[PDB]
Image (spheres, rainbow, N blue to C red):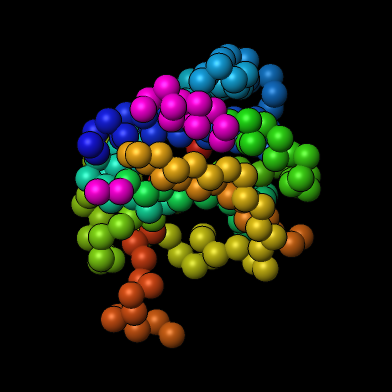
């Protein structure tokens, strides 16, 4: 059911987000402590403000996952000019065994650990943001994600979302009885009609993460 996969996914997304920040050098290696999750070595941040920022973000995603209202969670890497330079897209599906999915989840971690060998180096001084693509028909009502008053979300703009002539690097795909998920990276090369079924609700936290 929705609450079981919500717990599992948010636990996993926190780990994966921490790791992405490490391997893409968004924060210095010196803030990261090695740990083990799903029997794989991971890097977790010890920066309490960064950690709270990631937990607040995922605390707003979690009730959306519980209602099966999440299509994508995306970590965007922005260069110091605030242009997206990399996107880590977690495409999530909950169709209508845990130790099996933890082994399946572990595979995502392993592929993130090697993406720095295929992704080209990021310019210095990148920051990150998170995008959430929801599932239900798109309207301007944000109330379902505004679950923390002091952690506001704002609707994303085309510039926030759509990468410029992107190189596509899939990392990992899983299929399970209760969860299907695809992780891929978009790397920068370096009609708007109301009835359009491609219309999307996409939101990002208004607050920026702690500077590095």
Q: Quadrant of residue 111?
A: top right
136 to the left or right of 102 = left
Residue 14 visible in the current orientation: no
Write the start and end of the magenta stretch as one range.
95-108
Whole-percent x, y for residue 61 in the image: 33, 41
Q: Main secondary structure of the magenta part?
A: helix
User: Relative to 77, does residue 30 appear above or below in the rendering?
Assistant: above
Whole-percent x, y for residue 211 in the image: 58, 35
203 to the left or right of 168 = left
Identify which residue is drawn at 74% across, 39% down. 116
Q: In which quarter of the image is residue 139?
A: bottom left
Identify which residue is drawn at 33% across, 75% down. 197
Identify which residue is drawn at 69% across, 60% down. 167
For the C terminus, the image quarter is: top right
User: Relative to 203, does residue 17 appear above or below in the rendering?
Assistant: above
Identify which residue is drawn at 67% across, 31% down. 113
Q: Does the magenta stretch include residue 106?
A: yes
Whole-percent x, y for residue 147 in the image: 24, 41
């Amino acid at each position: 059911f929705g609450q079981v996969v919500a717990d599992v996914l948010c636990e996993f997304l926190e780990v994966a987000v921490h790791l992405i920040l490490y391997v893409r050098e968004v924060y210095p290696v010196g803030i990261f402590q090695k740990r083990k999750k799903y029997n794989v070595p991971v890097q977790m941040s010890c920066h309490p403000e960064l950690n709270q920022y990631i937990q607040d973000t995922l605390h707003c995603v979690k009730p959306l996952l519980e209602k099966n209202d999440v299509e994508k969670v995306v970590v965007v890497i922005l260069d110091k000019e605030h242009r997206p330079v990399e996107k880590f897209v977690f495409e999530i599906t909950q169709p209508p065994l845990l130790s099996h999915v933890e082994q399946l989840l572990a595979a995502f971690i392993l592929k993130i650990s090697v993406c720095d060998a295929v992704l080209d180096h990021n310019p210095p001084g990148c920051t990150f943001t998170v995008l959430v693509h929801t599932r239900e028909a798109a309207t301007r009502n944000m109330e379902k994600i505004q679950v923390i008053k002091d952690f506001p979300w704002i609707l994303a703009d085309e510039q926030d979302v759509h990468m410029h002539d992107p190189r596509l690097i899939p990392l990992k795909t899983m299929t399970s009885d209760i969860l299907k998920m695809q992780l891929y990276v978009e790397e920068r090369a370096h009609s708007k009609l109301i009835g359009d079924p491609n219309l999307e609700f996409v939101a990002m936290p208004a607050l920026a993460p702690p500077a590095s």
